[PDB]
Image 1: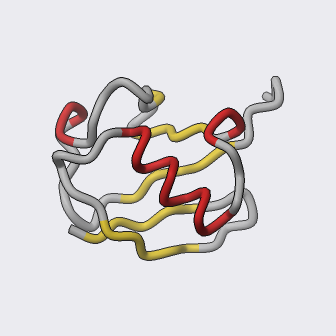
Image 2: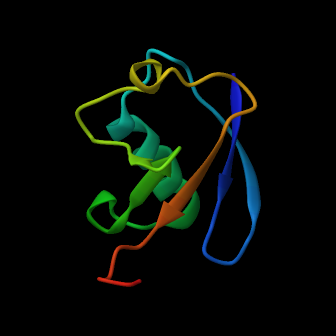
Length: 76
């Protein structure tokens, strides 16, 4: 299934992922697009912060789902 990723600028990207995919792999796809190390990547879905140890299916993620990416710099 294809998902939409949002950046800090408000850009919508179409990436291909699967329920059997692990958060880690996800961050890898973003890196190849944004070029930012997972150490500075932060995915927040439905308020919850996806962990590099869990997967998409873990959070009952479906197709057409959108996720927000963050840099993580003690902001807020």
